[PDB]
Image (tube, coloured by chain):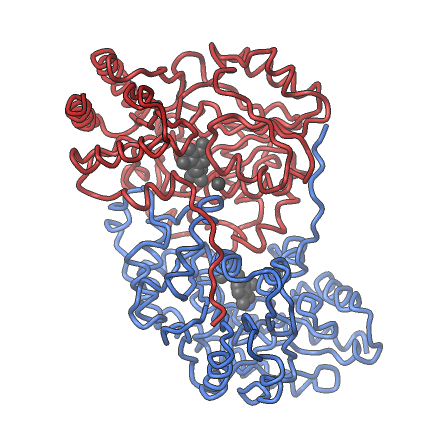
Chain colours: A blue, B red
Amino acid sequence: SSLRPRREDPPVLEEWYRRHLGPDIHDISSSGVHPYSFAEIRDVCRIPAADLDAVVMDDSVSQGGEGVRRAIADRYAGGDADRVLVTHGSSEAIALTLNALLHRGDRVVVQEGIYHSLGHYPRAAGCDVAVLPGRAVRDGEIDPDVLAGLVTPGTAAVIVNFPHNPTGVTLSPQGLRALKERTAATGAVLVWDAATAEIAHRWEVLADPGADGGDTVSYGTLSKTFGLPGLRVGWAVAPKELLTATFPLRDRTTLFLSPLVELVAERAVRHADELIGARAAEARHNLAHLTGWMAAHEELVRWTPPEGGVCALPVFRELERAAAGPQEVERFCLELLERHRTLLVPGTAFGAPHGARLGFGGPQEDFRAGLDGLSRFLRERA
Amino acid sequence: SSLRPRREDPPVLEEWYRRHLGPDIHDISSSGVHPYSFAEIRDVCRIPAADLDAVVMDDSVSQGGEGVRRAIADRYAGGDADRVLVTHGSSEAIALTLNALLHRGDRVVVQEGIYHSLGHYPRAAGCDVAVLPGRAVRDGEIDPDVLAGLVTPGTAAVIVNFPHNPTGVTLSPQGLRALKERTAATGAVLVWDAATAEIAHRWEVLADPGADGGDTVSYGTLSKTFGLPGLRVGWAVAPKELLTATFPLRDRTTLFLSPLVELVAERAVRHADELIGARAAEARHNLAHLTGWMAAHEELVRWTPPEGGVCALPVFRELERAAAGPQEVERFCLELLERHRTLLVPGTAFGAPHGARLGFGGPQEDFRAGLDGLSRFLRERA
Ligand SMILES: Cc1ncc(COP(=O)(O)O)c(C=O)c1O
Ligand SMILES: Cc1ncc(COP(=O)(O)O)c(C=O)c1O
Ligand SMILES: [Au+]
Ligand SMILES: [Au+]
């Protein structure tokens, strides 16, 4: 037969979860907040059974249901619905837009250690790619000298995710303001992933660049801060001109969304503050206990604390002392899972060989035991 | 700025609906049955509010929720769940699988007049494409001489949709049995879209080739026969070996489905017969009235009656008499819409210049007026 499936490697992050995610374990690896039950959702976002039952299971539209597009636009695009594309999670948004945006040849600046599919599509589009290093961003700004060197006239796009999954680095309202001007001046397009935007620790929550009305693309999703990764709804905020040029590709992949799923999402974006607040507040209870845990263990673990989001990237000192290979952290994260029922994401997924993703977005009531698992783990090896 | 959106033409079918679909009109253009309300769905498929509310809005899995994969597998894959991939409508299934299946160079046989994205992906994959003509399939079999010529050793895949959207041509259990053997013998992969599979008029409902356990790919969806185009759930039935090789692409596009949407779909596939039966029976009430309407108008309209599905392709004699250009049918379908509030899909979407898609899957209670609209329309021009 001619059944030869094309061999492409799975991205480290997804394959890790596929292989190891399951029940009977203390999971502290997620870059998002722990999910709500659908019960809770109807209660918080105010959804009667009669409103769901009234939904005709018919075709939605290409750009997204008018109701839910209004809800996102108001919050993120300054009322302009024509500038929102609603997608099957922000993943579909990234795929559709970047496909329509990037050409072969163009110079594109991509944040180091970025979530794959954001660096994946420019790499695929055969773009000329120049890395914006991790160390270049500190104290809520990108070294203006590094910005001058990397983003010059001609440059097609600058792709960044802030707050950063997994490190938890982000920008000050000034830092973003500088970056906007740099890209406005060179003609570059700011591509801006705002997945964990709503949870900020050091500075105030960053206003969406897509709200300006300029030549920028920004993404958002109900999956990280909202506690609805399983609703599968995200968006892109960008010029109508681009969004409509994504339709042909949508026509051979997904077509459109469920008006039922849209109904729900519309109410989630309206009652967003109630949804995020309860989870953010909970996550900081966790952050506090983590910081103490960190200082108690500073002989074995070094870290930069998150300036945003609900996950960090602790670095284990023993992997720096041996120094490579990257395969070690995976063995580490495996042994941690087998002996103590505790999950992290090995840093090989984020170009941080010595690091690992520790997420504190989950339930307070352990949480704690994952740490107590890792604590027991770290002592045994030393 | 560098915001130059890549210019790709929208497929005729989708852009037609985008431009012209709306309210205040009699729509008789759909290749599927008219949709259910979510109320009706909970009533028919037996879904209490307490079962929905119990759903944690968390991550589903890559291949699809075990519950809903069982429901499809039992009905379509002979119990084997490992052979089902559940996707955002069959559209995602076609995209994921064909991407993983087709290589550059291979010879692929593609049914004439096929729904775009089925012919789109082999064309994209740079495959060597040879058309299987419309006239080659009649009386529930493909001319065995045409099969001998087109599907020879080496041939990578044969892509077909039966019953055919829009013509409504399909196969006898013998016709499919012949086609299976031809492809089994040459080593070719049968790619088989079974969207409108459950509604058959001339022969019995075609058993799913994916149930054999051989090297075949078959698609299915709750969108055409089930009355749930707005639930956005379809599947592929194929070897686990292929389906798992689609994961990398899913990881940069959609990730997975909603466990809430899966819960619903699981109950829809179990109560499938109740869902289809009420719509099939209704559609045949419509077919009967259409056949009479057809014979009453045989001076202006010629057609082959559907052997399956809920749409046909009537041919208007005036477009054959003038003979081209293809742009005429669109003017026709536009003028029909403007003067009489009646929608069809102009045949330019299916490589049938003189034809137009008339769907009889909609509500009985006009229905009739669309015909009475088209009747009034046809007389005026002659
Ligand atoms: C920054 C970022 N963007 C996007 C995604 C994909 O999520 P979704 O498609 O639910 O928005 C993830 C999940 O790992 C993420 O961390
Ligand atoms: C044969 C066929 N397959 C697939 C589709 C896409 O539908 P879905 O993605 O809902 O399965 C259509 C809709 O026009 C169709 O006619
Ligand atoms: Au990727
Ligand atoms: Au297409």
Q: Nearer the viewer, residue A18 or B50?
A: A18
Q: Position of residue B204 (x, y in %)?
A: 45, 14
- Locate residue A30 relative to residue A207 in the image: left or right: right
Q: Residue B26 at x, y = what percent? A: 20, 34
Q: Name the residue: 60% across, 86% down.
A: A292
Where is residue A39, by image quadrant?
bottom left
Q: Which residue of the protein is positioned furthest toward the right in this rendering? A: A322
On the image, which quarter does residue A241 sit in? bottom left
Q: Is residue A193 above or below residue B276?
A: below
Instruction: Check the image and name the residue furthest to the front.
Output: B322
Q: Quadrant of residue A209?
A: bottom left
Quadrant of ligand 3 in image? bottom right
Q: Is residue B18 left or right of residue B351?
A: left
* Residue B219 pos. (x, y %): 52, 32
Residue A180, compared with residue B245, is above or below; it is below
Q: Is residue A236 visible?
A: yes
With respect to residue A125, does B33 lie above or below? Answer: above
Residue drawn at (59%, 40%), measured in percent from left and top? Answer: B97
Q: Nearer the viewer, residue B56 or B129?
A: B129
Of the 4 image quadrants, the one containing the N terminus of chain A is top right
Q: At 70% across and 33% down in the image, what residue appears? A: A3
